[PDB]
Length: 261
Ligand SMILES: Nc1ncnc2c1ncn2[C@@H]1O[C@H](CSCC[C@H](N)C(=O)O)[C@@H](O)[C@H]1O
Image 1 (tube, rainbow, N blue to C red):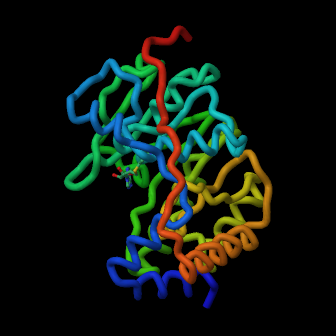
Image 2 (image 1 turned 135 degrees about the vertical axis):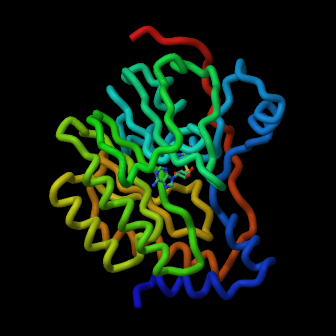
């Protein structure tokens, strides 16, 4: 019924070539060539990011959509690109990363970029059921894509319900993935969270056109419904006239070393 749902139905109708051409049209991409090189070698003394995902939190951080500070929780940390980025920030005290790391799911990668000494990881951890702990900064990049919209809305809702469970009164800063923001249920859940916590929803330009994902962040205020539809219209406009060409940016590179306090 919504414009986003129309986008989803049209995406599921594209052929391979149409799909591949559409998914990169006018998006932004990091050059991952250097990092792939060193990750294959197995080098831990070079200042690369363990994931493509780090580019998203850098963008949000540098643009002022969120502050990164104090005790940091990274829920669904995967390889740990959000965790290592956080640990290199001078206002950051400690970083704790939780992820599944089971069959098919990625595990934490050990790296020695700046502040590695104040990062701790735990796999075999389900953030939906495990006990919560306090934080000043709460991060969550969870939300697996699906061609089924009802699967996407269920995964999204579950992420948002768990975020509310995790958020502490000290948690002034937050960044939560919203996989399928086009669903009316998801809009209603976001509006209700916003009433309590403030903040707003944003589209990160590093997301491919083949996902409608957006991020619920703490450092901006906006109209949820208007922001979701502005992205839907944008994703629809690109589908009609796909450029096939992405913007390339330099990757997330960090210093190495330990940090004091
Ligand atoms: N219920 C759950 N509990 C813990 N981790 C989960 C989870 N559901 C999904 N995940 C994990 O969440 C991760 C999202 S990918 C994380 C990317 C990360 N921001 C980075 O830059 O590296 C996946 O690895 C998936 O295994």
